[PDB]
Length: 164
Ligand code: NA
Ligand code: NA
Ligand code: NA
Image (spheres, rainbow, N blue to C red):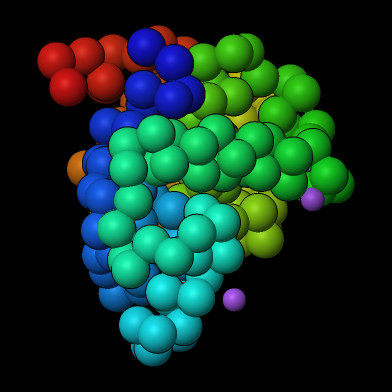
């Protein structure tokens, strides 16, 4: 298991524009196009992201290319963030993937504000951090995904992604 396979499990793969769990136009492996309610706006975002007139449909290779970019943008945003970088730097490779997953889903700004959960992760108080992370809108709105990510932080293993 690795960050690509992990996010592929959590985000799925769809080749036509769809609405994500928040109702926002998305394509591929969780590539958010726009928060605008306009499908036309989403289509402009898509054609711009792919570099051609897509008519709302892409190939698997194109989806994987956006995913390459999006995973790196999650990492780059962690490293540029004064609250997230020290946590990321303190973590092992598996738990780093859990943090990347959170940032991919919710954005740098939101995760960076979880000052108690971040402190507990930095302190390597894994069970405490896991309890604290579950006191979140994130956990309540996407509990199965959050449980997998939280188990990854709690254990430092990929056990929650086995058989998926
Ligand atoms: Na545009
Ligand atoms: Na940043
Ligand atoms: Na603990």
